[PDB]
Image 1: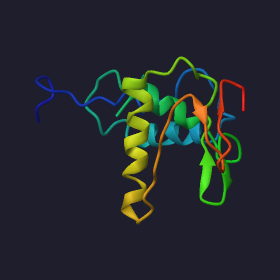
Image 2: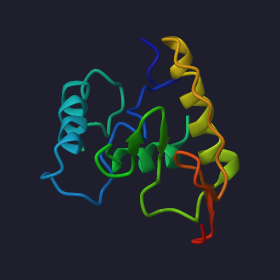
Image 3: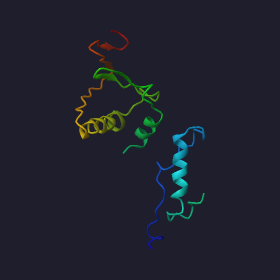
Image 4: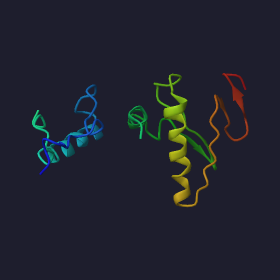
Length: 48
Length: 80
């Protein structure tokens, strides 16, 4: 109800760091939770 | 509460980077090492350790310095 004044974005620790690939197993779960809590946020760039 | 501190922990296991014996033990960090911010990383890792053990009675007694104590055989800078 307040996007445009305050937009919730995903945190900078929400993301797996851009180095290690998907073979890193606990780096894969940080991508799974990032997808389920993706459209809950109000960032318009959150699909990307 | 530290972006850098969190990054260091993730790549750390307990089969590597920890040697348990008795009640003693040495926790040796991952190789993003000497370059360690004592204000941000190594002290905030310690207070979250000493409060971790207090939530179930284990009074952890940490004393980090660049020597190493392991069942009463000290060694400073690669020299026993």
